[PDB]
Image (tube, rainbow, N blue to C red; front, side, top):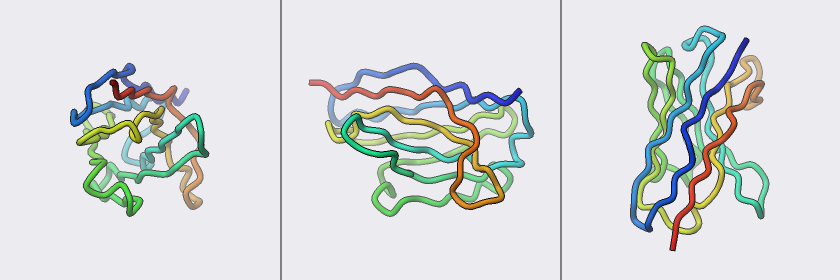
Length: 120
């Protein structure tokens, strides 16, 4: 029933911004927070932050503040993440993941992911 539909992959020149979407369905959108997570091939999953649709409350990993920007549109059941001033370090697959409250940072559902590539 639940699904998280992410936007398609982007190829971008350095210094570009990108804005990516995560369209939720099969559940009440304001009932759950939406996490975002970064995955490089060389590393484990890295939490970026989450937004709570019900009150637009955000919480960020300290390294991603001023880099990532999380927003949400309740009417369209859609989370968004904007990444600015992209560099090669930003090249990764990015996932939205529904917060399984309770409890904690646990994430019960995941989007298919959005590959961002910075080149050259």
